Image (cartoon, coloured by chain):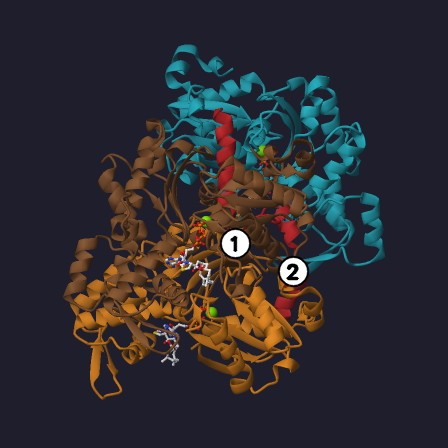
Chain colours: A orange, B cyan, C brown, D red
Amino acid sequence: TALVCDNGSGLVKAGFAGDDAPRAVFPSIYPIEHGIITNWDDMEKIWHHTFYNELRVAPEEHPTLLTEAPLNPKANREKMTQIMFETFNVPAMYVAIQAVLSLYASGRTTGIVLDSGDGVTHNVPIYEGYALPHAIMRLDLAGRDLTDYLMKILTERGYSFVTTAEREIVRDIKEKLCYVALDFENEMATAASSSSLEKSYELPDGQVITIGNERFRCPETLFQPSFIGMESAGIHETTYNSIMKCDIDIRKDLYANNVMSGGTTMYPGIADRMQKEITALAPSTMKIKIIAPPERKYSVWIGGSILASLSTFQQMWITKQEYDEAGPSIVHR
Amino acid sequence: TALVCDNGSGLVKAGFAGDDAPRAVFPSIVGSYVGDEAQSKRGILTLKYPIEHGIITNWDDMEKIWHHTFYNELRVAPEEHPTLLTEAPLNPKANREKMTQIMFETFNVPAMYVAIQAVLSLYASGRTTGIVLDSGDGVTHNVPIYEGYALPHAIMRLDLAGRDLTDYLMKILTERGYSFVTTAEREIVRDIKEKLCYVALDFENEMATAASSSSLEKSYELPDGQVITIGNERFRCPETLFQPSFIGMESAGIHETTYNSIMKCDIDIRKDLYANNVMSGGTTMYPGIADRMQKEITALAPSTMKIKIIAPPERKYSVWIGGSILASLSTFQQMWITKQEYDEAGPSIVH
Amino acid sequence: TALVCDNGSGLVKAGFAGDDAPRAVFPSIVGSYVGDEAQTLKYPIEHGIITNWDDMEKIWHHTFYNELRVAPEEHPTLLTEAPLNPKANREKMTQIMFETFNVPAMYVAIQAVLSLYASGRTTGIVLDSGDGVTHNVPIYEGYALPHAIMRLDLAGRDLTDYLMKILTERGYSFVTTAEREIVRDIKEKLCYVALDFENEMATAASSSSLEKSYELPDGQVITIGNERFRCPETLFQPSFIGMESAGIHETTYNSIMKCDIDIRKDLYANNVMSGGTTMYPGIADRMQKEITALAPSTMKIKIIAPPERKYSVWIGGSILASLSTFQQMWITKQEYDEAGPSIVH
Amino acid sequence: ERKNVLQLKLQQRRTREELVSQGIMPPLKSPAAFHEQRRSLERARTEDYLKR
Ligand SMILES: Nc1ncnc2c1ncn2[C@@H]1O[C@H](COP(=O)(O)OP(=O)(O)OP(=O)(O)O)[C@@H](O)[C@H]1O
Ligand SMILES: Nc1ncnc2c1ncn2[C@@H]1O[C@H](COP(=O)(O)OP(=O)(O)OP(=O)(O)O)[C@@H](O)[C@H]1O
Ligand SMILES: Nc1ncnc2c1ncn2[C@@H]1O[C@H](COP(=O)(O)OP(=O)(O)OP(=O)(O)O)[C@@H](O)[C@H]1O
Ligand SMILES: C/C1=C/C(=O)O[C@@H]2C[C@@H](CC[C@H](C)/C=C\CC1)O[C@@](O)([C@@H]1CSC(=O)N1)C2
Ligand SMILES: C/C1=C/C(=O)O[C@@H]2C[C@@H](CC[C@H](C)/C=C\CC1)O[C@@](O)([C@@H]1CSC(=O)N1)C2
Ligand SMILES: C/C1=C/C(=O)O[C@@H]2C[C@@H](CC[C@H](C)/C=C\CC1)O[C@@](O)([C@@H]1CSC(=O)N1)C2
Ligand SMILES: [Mg+2]
Ligand SMILES: [Mg+2]
Ligand SMILES: [Mg+2]
């Protein structure tokens, strides 16, 4: 049996090729920033924890597939492969791009992915299983950011939230009460006219806070980065631009296959919002389909599982023999 | 800002001077309704192609397509933009006169220029000398060019191109057992072509391989779920480009025509040509074509001659891009036929 | 495949023409041991110039054989060099490449230029600021305008030293070489450029919002405040470390103003920042504010600071070296054999 | 299940080489990302040429 390890900036999703969902999901504590490994010691630690604590396996007995971010430096994956083979004496290993695996989980090999987790967001167009690197769009606005923003504007409402623990509480509030407005201005107006949009949340200390327009002002950032002082464009605009950087002939194939994946895409309404905006941007004769499977917070991992189970995939593994002959570099081929 | 309009037999490529890829690309058909508008409403629409083999042959439907371009796809006021149109090698002067007229009178453009497609291709590659193979949906040309000027006597027209290769594909695909004959079925086959066809380095060797196994076999899903299997057909189709006889043409293949074209040029410039084969157009997009042309031209050309086949990935759009580039050049702005100039001189002034 | 070697005063960036990042990045030092292996220390490169050909031969060897794992005779190699690099120096570079490493072919390019290329431009002014030197290098249609280049011996290492000093002034002892590395870490992780220095100083006087904490390896945890910005402010106010020179904004400006007036607009609209010392948060905006305040009021100012920029020089190299059309620029071993070192010029 | 469909597709797919040749992928050893910028240079040079 093979292992599947989706090494995220906020959560590790680990499991066994085969399963419909990862056996283990635990905080990535932060060795990973914005999707890139930046502390190999703490990373070795996290991997060790994964193999020995959460999965309860002998790494030398399992081929292992790890995920990686779009735009991940080759030196990076080389270091990954090395650590895998030398530190954990794994039999075989493979590294795959997250967005791609997301796409695979949806039963596609072509389309554009919006992958947005805790620390980074990507638009990754993909044709016949290959990412079009030149069209990828990184955006350093994600889960953690939206949480911080929530702490700020919540404070502005009168509630103090600033400590690390207070930050975790706010994150809970976010996941449980935030959502994307179909129309931001209209929603703000409604929020001004009544208390229908207002919801209540109980803190651990019993006290019970009330959150209103914040509920959707928060995720609104994903579309209006200026809210947190970013000069960048919104996820809709980046999707669009990404498509518009792709060979025009395949753009239709892209438009008809928007796959959303990751924790920060879980907001109710985001799908529809993206449909409305892309529609407003895209040619009027183009078909737009936004795919947001309920499973999607784990779709990257699932993609991995699926890929790794395919008999036909078994010929893609970098084996310990192959590593022994060729060295880290072999991962690139 | 100027407009750039590459009016092809199958696709219109329109955009703004300065951009590296045309803003709009749509079928050159008028069902009245244009483009994908016409593509959707197929049941109620009858499709016609105003451009055949690179030449405009229906000025009414052409006026239509242009209108669509300006007003629907580009969203501009034609009177506010100088416009550069493309044209085919061997385009009759009367033709360009009619173009200029329609441009100035029907669309009240401020200024306009007409350029030869192959040439613009060449420009996009940063050259002003070399021979172009321009092969689109309805016609193929070998156009030798020296210091920006086409050598008309050495041009070679060949009425074998994209659409032809698609038809051939429908035929031999049928011969394999799959029915494909209706218009829609033709579009599906075209998809198959673009996605699965390629040129063999060596036709006979490839046929042998295709006989010995299923490595060359690939699968394609039709819209109705059913999934067909295509093998040697994958490479026989575009081989046509080298063996026109396959579809009953007495003509020579694109390699031979390139060669002959060169051999009709002033011998002194031939080296300059050989070292600068530029391929452009949708029908040059087959994987392997470049290499094939290198092998064949090598086999035909003197053994002391250097052969370079240039096939930029951008090439399906290189004509248009050439246009863009040309039109952006400050130094070019003095070449535009202005509405004043037209007013004084009449259509003829384009020449 | 070709090699790309950005030989810096502090870090070597080496890789393969064809890649988006350099495969290897290691300290430009020799202790004999080279690069990270070596971590008494020598820096063969000072202020962008090679000044110890033996240790340089060493570092190159390390690059080829240790970090890249290649046979130099099998790879065309592009090396970078600094603006204002002497004929003589590149002469010795070339000689060493062909004779000591029997490379098949090689090319030398100016760092700032490659930076510019990585941004998809062939005209504009570059501020390239690494560990040991800073340059303003105006470039018109691919050609550096040598007369308008501005060298400034104030860079990364300097800002680190300054940080050690003023940190000490706060009460924290930092003076040893190792202590210097620690401070460099602190710098990269906590320093930033104020949009305006006086306002920032005032804020730093009024509260502890600007204060940040850093953990040393020995567990102890220090607190750094206004120093966070006092440090980089040096780039704009060299007097802070007792330099009579002007700041990077003023040098950019002056550089432009030494250029043929007609191309100045082209320059203003294309300020490309590259190098480790340009990585401070806020520097871009600062440069926008200052240049704006200096430049004509009808001029458009654009400061381009790609996230990739600490490696943009190397990337420029990669790109240049991959261009089919470039392959005709390589100095070949044959060409060298006929013409001698001089041929590089 | 899903895995079966994905497998189907994965088997009947083009090599990066092919896709490059059809102009969907960039080369083919030429910083895939940063392609935008390479193409940008290319275009520049050719322009500088044509004006000259
Ligand atoms: N139901 C939800 N609604 C909104 N946000 C959510 C929800 N569930 C999780 N999140 C957010 O998703 C983010 C993390 O998810 P994810 O696991 O995809 O990050 P990651 O993949 O590990 O990080 P990265 O993608 O940057 O490598 C967290 O910020 C979390 O707050
Ligand atoms: N990957 C591909 N493989 C095979 N054929 C392709 C491919 N891509 C495009 N084509 C073909 O190229 C043809 C279109 O080329 P293009 O649109 O540039 O020329 P055109 O200007 O419309 O026609 P023409 O040059 O004859 O006036 C179409 O027939 C199309 O099917
Ligand atoms: N995030 C950062 N903030 C501030 N400085 C940084 C940061 N990252 C790297 N540096 C500094 O950049 C310097 C080295 O970067 P760089 O690789 O550009 O040097 P170099 O190019 O080899 O030197 P040179 O250009 O002078 O020849 C170091 O002084 C280092 O501390
Ligand atoms: C329940 C849970 C949610 C989560 O995703 O948390 C992960 C990991 C976490 C690490 C610190 C936290 C206290 C440890 C585990 C939390 C795990 O940081 C995050 O919450 C960050 C910090 S704020 C935010 O929104 N994301 C992401
Ligand atoms: C997708 C596409 C490709 C193309 O180039 O098609 C152009 C224009 C097109 C118009 C008819 C079609 C139903 C409308 C649009 C299809 C355009 O017909 C073509 O496909 C014909 C049919 S087979 C062929 O190669 N040319 C050429
Ligand atoms: C992490 C790192 C940064 C760096 O660029 O370091 C490069 C090279 C390095 C060489 C000696 C050092 C002890 C070895 C490795 C450090 C490399 O010193 C530097 O840090 C110098 C010394 S302090 C400073 O700011 N630059 C520059
Ligand atoms: Mg992730
Ligand atoms: Mg054409
Ligand atoms: Mg440098």
C200 vs B248, left or right, is left
Whether residue A65 is situated above or below residue C163 in the rendered picture: below
* Residue C291 location, quadrant: top left
Mark 2 Cβ and ligand 7 under 8 Å apart = no
| Pointer 2 with pointer 1, Cβ within 8 A | no
Report x, y in % for residue B319: 55, 33
x%, y% of residue A19? 57, 80
| Ligand 5 placement by image quarter | top right
Q: Amino acid at mark 1?
A: Lys
Q: Residue at x 53, y 64 (%)?
A: C38
Q: How far across and down, in percent of the image, does residue B320 sit?
A: 52, 34
Q: In this view of the protein, which residue sits in the foreground, B207 or B119?
A: B119
Chain identity of mark 2: A
Other-residue count near label 1 (Cα within 10 Å), few / some / many at <14 / 14–19 / ≥20: many
Rendered image quadrant of residue C214: bottom left
> Which residue lies under the disc numbered 2?
A333
Report how far apart the C-alphas of labels 2 and 1 lie in the structure. Answer: 22 Å
As displayed, is residue B94 above or below residue B197? above
Q: Numbered disc 1: what chain?
A: C
The residue pinned by badge 1 equals C13
Could you say which is closer to the camera, residue B127 or residue A48? Answer: A48
Query: Can residue A286 be seen here?
Result: no
Per the image, label 2 sits on a secondary structure element best described as: loop
- Left or right: C164 as drawn, with respect to B120: left
Locate the N terminus of chain B and report the quarter of the image it occupies.
top left
Are marks 2 and 1 in one subunit?
A: no
Identify whether C297 is placed above or below A168. above
Q: Ligand 3 within 8 A of label 1's CB?
A: yes
